[PDB]
Length: 221
Length: 221
Image (cartoon, one colour):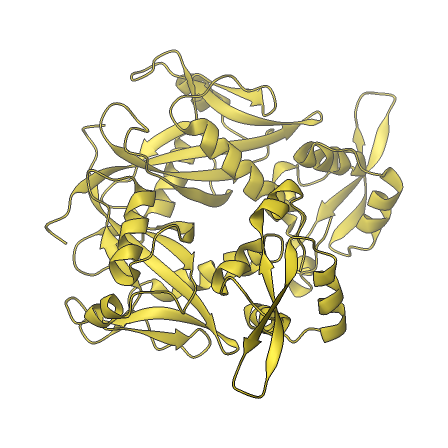
């Protein structure tokens, strides 16, 4: 153990949200050094008293004030010169949150903004490569697991769910087949509530229950 | 950067091979401390002069003498007490090699043995959890990419290819549909060579060319 070097261990969060048709990431225009004024993911460092997963949770809560967040580890990024300051190996995670539900004041302190995932600014270091990989993993996984519902409020319309999925895959779906495919899922249940987008339009709301899903975990959408 | 701790950065390789129907891992019965006499993955440590990926390659070559090996990063394992000695965060990779082709002498020095992935001994620390995750990733990926061919010699029979796939999924396939599905792949080409398993039996040999695959990269098996 002792003849080997030690490394600063970074945490970087790719924070996904969904709103009005598009998938956005929560990014920081850095107040601080290095690369001041440039865009980046939310970052921190693993501490001696916490696991790497717990560091991810802390860093995310620091920005958002959110806990019990769906998170996935993306990977350990460890090119020698990835960060020009000192050597840092960073573990990237992605997170899927409800965009109506984070802590606005914390976001303001970090000087963070939501940006459309298809219209991102240049990001520092190897952050573009972290985003690319997290996207692929998320697309891969959201086609066989119900992880997408973390991006939606507890109650959602089918129009929104469809729109979510079109945004995830950058491709429009057949409305007919989609609606059917959802009706065949018992754990996506139709409620007797409606979304009132303005005085003159409504739409039926659904909810996902993970009890019904976990008793029969079949998902493909 | 400087107010944060630094960590020993481990490398752990899950080394997959394929032979006579079954998938095996190359494991070490440790000559050395800690946990002497117990079974583990092949490990090392990231050095100051190498990227994390390059450390993975080195550690694997140390045991096998192999280079240009198909490898995938599995993840950063960072529970505080994962390794009871000092704190180590370890990056697990998996590797897919041709079992006829490694360096026997290096394997002997490390006191490593091939073991059936379904009949593994107890492994130390969080190595079981690394193996579990690498298996899932490998199964997931080998169903949509031609990564399986790294586990086979350059020339293979369809009987072997089938057998490989049955072992990957722990499930027998329909011989008929399988054979057809392969005929529909131009990049799996039939040669005029035969495997001579003993004096009295042969079978037609095929090869994968990644040129033909990369020009039209469609794979599902």
